[PDB]
Amino acid sequence: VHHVHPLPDSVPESEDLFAPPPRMQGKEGRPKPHIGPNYESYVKEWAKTVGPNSDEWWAAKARETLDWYDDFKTVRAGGFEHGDVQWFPEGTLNAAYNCLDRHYYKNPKKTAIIYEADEPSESREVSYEELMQETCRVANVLKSYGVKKGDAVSIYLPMTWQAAAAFLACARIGAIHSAVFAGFSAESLRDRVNDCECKVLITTDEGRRGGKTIATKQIVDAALQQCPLVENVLVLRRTGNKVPMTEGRDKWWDEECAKMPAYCPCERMASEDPLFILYTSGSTGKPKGVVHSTAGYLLGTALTLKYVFDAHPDDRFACMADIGWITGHSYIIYGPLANGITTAVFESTPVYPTPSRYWDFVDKWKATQLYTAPTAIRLLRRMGEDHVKNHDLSSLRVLGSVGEPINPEAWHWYNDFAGKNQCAIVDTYWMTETGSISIAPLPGAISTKPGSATFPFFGMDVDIIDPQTGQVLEGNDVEGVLVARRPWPSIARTVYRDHKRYLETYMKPYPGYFFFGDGAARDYDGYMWIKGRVDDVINVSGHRLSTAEVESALILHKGVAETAVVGCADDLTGQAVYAFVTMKPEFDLKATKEADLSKELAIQVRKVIGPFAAPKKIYLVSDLPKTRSGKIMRRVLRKIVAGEPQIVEEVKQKVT
Ligand SMILES: Nc1ncnc2c1ncn2[C@@H]1O[C@H](COP(=O)(O)OP(=O)(O)OP(=O)(O)O)[C@@H](O)[C@H]1O
Ligand SMILES: [Mg+2]
């Protein structure tokens, strides 16, 4: 008799609640959790971070977490309506000083970065001394190019450890870095280079990902022909293969840095000075250049890492994402290094050289936390349990998931093999615009449900609004759109040179609130469930269906690897459901007739969700359209099913 149901799972609801395991109880010599041991301990602290008397907690956390050059006087000001959000405005600091120097001064030999190379034998540890010295050399090179405080600098680097040095070198001198996924086309790179109006670009000669070569310098050359403002290009010699170099414009990273000293002073940045620009992926439309300031963002990534992953000084955090993504910004570089711990820069893929790469990595360095996306979790689950069953992995305590709703079926595989039912699973929900994790379980306090992000993080006061009325739905067992009531420190301050798009997208749909764009429900116990994008909702005869419902129901069928449902106009039901299903490679499509597989899928969905939710048509594909981030581009499939990289050719053909 609950209007809000959990995501479909093979495990019954009465046996599907997972309390913090002994590794997250301070047992076996593991570190004691910062928040624990139950839900009330989370609320007792969270209540200090929201409301009209939360300034005391935030002012204390800001001064305790970051090193300041000048103290602040005001804690917060501004709001959503005009986009004038301010946090600690009178304070001065530097991100590079907090992520490097202050930890170098205490323990220079401590490992800052575990550089897991594409080839495993080429991996090595990078100390804080080496990362700070290389950062200061690059900062000295940029200053010799005439880069000033507030100038934009484009970054087009793959997942090599020097990418963090390029990030922090810009932050050290007050330049706004704008990282772009290594592998984006010359057209995509050009649009982001021209939009930020940078005069300097940093890239490599070539990149190496999963035994493949990214011709980064060749792509830069093609883009820069239509980028008339770039005057200086710094090229890192990653592979050593012959690439074109333009005289005067292009210089070698190693030859420039060798001329510069190994220390560079820190520019004293105001709290609201812009730290970086990051362009979104654009799963729903044209990407926007999200701008984050300094103090609020840095404090948010520092606190979230410490509490969402229960990080302790000697931990080795392993976020396997790419720094072209906000996950890499906040939980590879800024978050982990601000806390002064060891972070991982993973250059390869989850299946190179073999699908055991994640776990050969975990046992080699004894990683204490793992952070990845559901697309990689569903990829390793598809390759069999024989790449995971015979590893140790006991060094881990917390496993993370970010980017999309994680199906309970994929949640359990993560829980059973990567954690061996001894790790806590943090389903972390947030956006590029939020800066830091918005809704996630605190691993030493929250009992988890497969597919639920649980409860909002410190400083986040979220509510559910009925989109039909624009009113907040009070209580539990409610469903609607997710919004936030007040600003938080790490919130995006603007969209670069397009503040109107920033207010129209996030601040004007529901005035007084921040609009995430996601559908959400709060069950009877108060747990939040992110149902999917509001744009991706399908309305069949007045039944509003989310993507996470049907896809989680479809994956409950044997052999199903990954699915994606989109809507299309129907004359009887208003909209009809179309399913794109990917089976495991070992599945026999000849012994099992396809028409009977579709019928079994339609009954599997009807038995878990309802009669209305059965897909009207089901297409079998080899893969789905996905961004470099890993998100499924359901907007593309919807247009194909309506008539309007290489996987798009297989989808358009099979749709006719
Ligand atoms: N843990 C999660 N659970 C559910 N959805 C998630 C989770 N983490 C991320 N998401 C989804 O990802 C979105 C944020 O993704 P990101 O900021 O990388 O860009 P995007 O939404 O793909 O971009 P665009 O708005 O330009 O289309 C969220 O709004 C949500 O839809
Ligand atoms: Mg979005």
Image: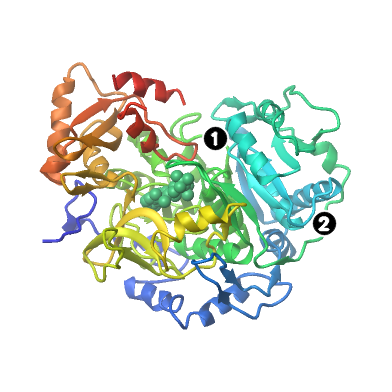
Where in the figure is residue 271, as x and y percent of width and height? 66, 68
Front residue of 604 and 467 = 467
Front residue of 413 and 322 = 322
51 left or right of 303 in image: left
For the residue labelled by badge 2, is the local secondary structure a helix, a strand or a loop? loop
The crowding category of the residue bearing disc 1, from other C-alpha atoms within 10 Å (few below 14, some 14 to 19, many at least 20), is: many
Residue 136 has which mark?
none
Q: Report whether the residue tagged 1 is closer than 8 Å to ligand 1.
A: no
Say which residue appears at 73% left-offset and 56% top-offset. Answer: 150
On the image, numbered disc 2 is attached to which residue?
A: 264
Q: Report whether the residue tagged 2 is closer than 8 Å to ligand 1.
A: no
256 left or right of 549 in image: right
Residue 86 location, quadrant:
bottom right
- Picture layout, residue 383 above or below residue 262: above
Q: Nearer the viewer, mark 2 or mark 1?
A: 2
Q: Looking at this rendering, what residue extends furthest in the top direction? A: 590
On the image, numbered disc 1 is attached to which residue?
A: 348
Where in the figure is residue 602, as x and y percent of width and height? 15, 34
Q: CA distance from mark 2 to mark 1?
A: 32 Å
Residue 85 location, quadrant:
bottom right
Say which residue appears at 43% left-offset and 34% top-offset. Answer: 626
Q: Amino acid at mark 2?
A: Cys
